[PDB]
Amino acid sequence: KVQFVIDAVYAMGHALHAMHRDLCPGRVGLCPRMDPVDGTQLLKYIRNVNFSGIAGNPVTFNENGDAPGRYDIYQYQLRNDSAEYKVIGSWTDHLHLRIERMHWLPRSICSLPCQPGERKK
Amino acid sequence: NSIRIDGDITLGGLFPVHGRGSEGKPCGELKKEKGIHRLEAMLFALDRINNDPDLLPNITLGARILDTCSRDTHALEQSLTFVQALIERV
Amino acid sequence: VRGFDRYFSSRTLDNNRRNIWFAEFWEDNFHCKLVKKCTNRERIGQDSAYEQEG
Amino acid sequence: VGVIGASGSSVSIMVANILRLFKIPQISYASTAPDLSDNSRYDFFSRVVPSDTYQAQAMVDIVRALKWNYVSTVASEGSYGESGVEAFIQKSREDGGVCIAQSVKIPREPKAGEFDKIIRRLLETSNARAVIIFANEDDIRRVLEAARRANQTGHFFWMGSDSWGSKIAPVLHLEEVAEGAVTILPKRMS
Image 1 (spheres, each protein chain N blue to C red):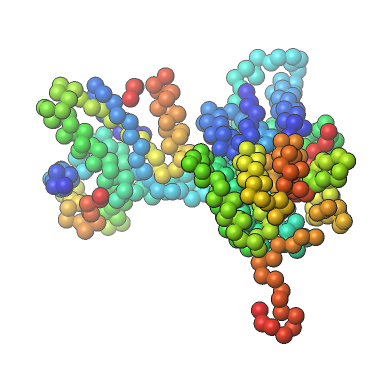
Image 2 (image 1 turned 90 degrees about the vertical axis):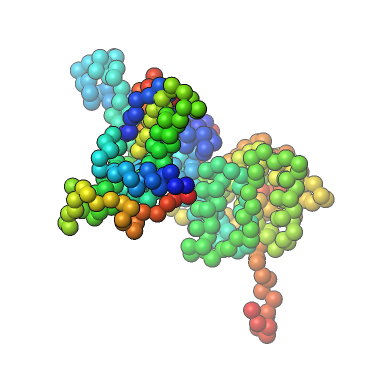
């Protein structure tokens, strides 16, 4: 989450810089008209921030206020040498699971398929 | 607006005058059976307390009713306006 | 509780000021703007919509 | 001129509504609750992390790829846990067909021993080998500690939420009982 904190404060700084450039184009440094700060005026630039983050990922901007990023699936298992969270695959608009890298396959089923073709389910 | 009764002691009030609004309007139709009845109840209670010589003699109770619209955002906005007006006293 | 019943039946609502929402209540209760317009002599006790709330 | 959001979803909701009252923007980093993504109630809550709807979609995609259909929802109070378990239930009933054994919640201040019953209600049903958790670090560690007791080790795996995607706090009970626990975490980098 620290990368997210850094990206958030960098987006706020970029929004402040864009607001200073737009409201005060020919004024270097602090601008006198920027002292009465407004939440809507700052949000209008926060919702339009677009820059290269620290991890190379562009902070997307939208009218909703969310960033559609990937959700990496990690797993913590014991390897008898060094136990840590291992990543599986990316989430470029769909699933990218990798076989033979999970569960050192245990399956949770509500009712076992007992009938092999003779009994009823 | 809001109901404001001048008195020595002010009592705030949150009453759902309007109903839950849709995505277009913040406040819906006026709750005639829920909000207005409780409003009249509190007003009658305050009047009977002020007219009661045994309970709180020579002390008048005010009123600080505010519009709720059964919505948490509007009620919190009204509470913010109340705090800003205080910083009268309730 | 007969006290609130008497206070709501005897006292009329259109006369008492300082209650801004009571105007809209009277407007949407009689189903007419202030079309099927009505007069100020009408009361709520005669209306079947008045029910004592717990 | 602008406040940075909080971690807990309830605290984040509180500060978000209070700061949008006074017209001040807010950017969060660890509050992915879906009820905070609407522009009508939290218009000043532009966060930099995706919501829990994508998390529930990821959970249902994982339980589809792992061929899992019987799971048990558990979470603590606050907007985070309830919103996450509701989003997971909705995404599972929408098209995945996965149903839920039981939905038991963890109280705020459990007294006189009301925590062993939570894990007993999950151990009494052996078919629920999959458990999706949505609590914070404290309640998750307490659930893992309660599951480690009663002579139980590796009975059922845990589907970890965003609360402990890559946290080092719950790795002790993981090496103890919760071996091979699967969690989720948004795309980041060192």
